[PDB]
Length: 116
Length: 115
Length: 116
Length: 115
Image (cartoon, rainbow over all chains, first blue to last red; front, side, top):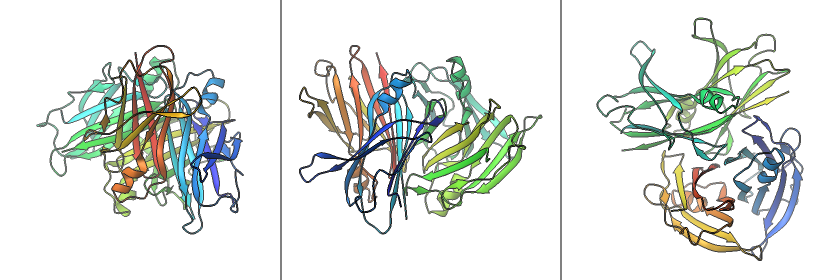
């Protein structure tokens, strides 16, 4: 159903990271990043419905997570401007991508869960 | 130095100083016997826990006292402590660096094992 | 509903970590760890139904995740015997705990998501 | 040394050797201008990227070429590269250590900022 989902967690509060802006880009033929989809994480730290199976073709995608704005709204001084997750989407049978990001003011981790 | 612990603070972006660390070794009776202990330095490092002679094969548990660290900084954390349990020197002596990255509700640990 | 859930992900395969044994213990008055609940992660890497709101009283709990057996079944030589997550469960209004663990052969990370 | 990069391999429990790193600085026209580059050593460290004089205030992007690293090891990874984007030296000169921990489908990055 949903081919690309983003989950964001807050490692300082131990909670979902709510209202985090997320911008997805697709690399164009001229090597520039073209806006593809965007949204804000929900109360559960999830962002669903970014794209459809039809539109999400093979290509290089960048998921930018606006971490600095998130920390600033919480009164915390962070290190990063934003987190970037860059990957190739490949048709190798049925696939769904979940990008999980765990945020700390001076650190972050990201993991991809790719399922059939 | 066959066993070292390095600890970083992901909130401050700095070494985690004065973090207590207790190391245990599993005895023949399956209990955890105290093996070594210390506190991280201003660089977040803890050296000199043991010697090549004393660090024989066995199952070791490195307990990093993260709750006491966060409490001293006025932060109420989730975990009591981080626990790193591993078999050491089962294919001969190795040097181990246990790296820990701390957040109030999360931590990560990684081992760098060198021959 | 479910007060304690465990999620386990595999950072080498980018997938849920399936059939991972998980043992939960509660610290007794004599300072020993008493078995409390156990199970295996599902096809989604989740373990639900470990306990009930009635049984999950305030106390110190240890969640042991049998990572070495998981890696060995995949033909991978890991560092840790198991991962341990030790925490105090506190009544501070309605609370649900999700313990998330991300596994690599020589590293792991754990995060707690505590919600109302 | 005001900017250093340390990279670890979470699969092998070892430093990640020969990892290419490219650093960019945001120009007045909002484009990313090449700033410095290098490869991690046998210890997983990359030193000497820049000097205190050249490392002025600005927004920097440290690109760690993780896909090329995993491909050279016969592992097909998820990410193209890891990207660490930050404002540097906005309250005066600081020393930055960017630490990255790599797995085929995951990575973590942490910054240690010292004055």
